[PDB]
Image 1 (cartoon, one colour):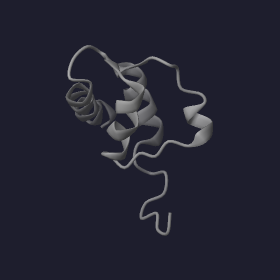
Image 2 (tube, helix red, strand yellow):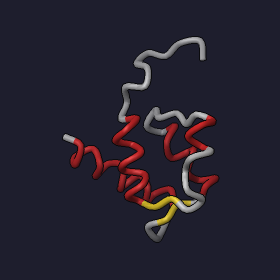
Image 3 (cartoon, helix red, strand yellow):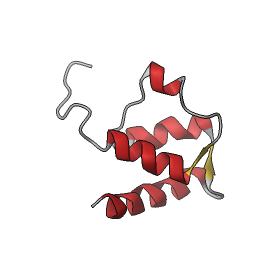
Image 4 (cartoon, rainbow, N blue to C red):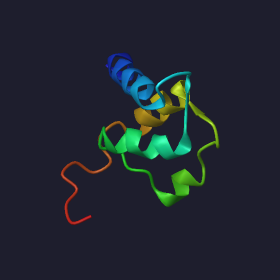
Amino acid sequence: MASDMEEKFREAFILFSSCSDHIEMYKFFELMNSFGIILTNDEKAALPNDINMDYWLNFAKKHYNYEQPFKHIN
C-alpha cells in the first residue's frame, strides 16, 4: 500500500538528508534514482526550491515505479 511504501521513502529521505525534514536539492535527485524514479526537465522546473518529506512522499506517489518498467536504451 502507498503508506507502507511511504515508510521506505521516509527512511531513505532521512538517510540522504542526514537530519531535518528537508532535503538539499543536490542530494534530492540522487535520492530518487535510488528508487528508480526519474525527474524530467518540466518537473524539475516545477519542484519548490525547498523540498520536504511530504513533497517527496507525494511526488513518489505520482511516479511510484511505473513511469516505464524496463525502460531500455535511455
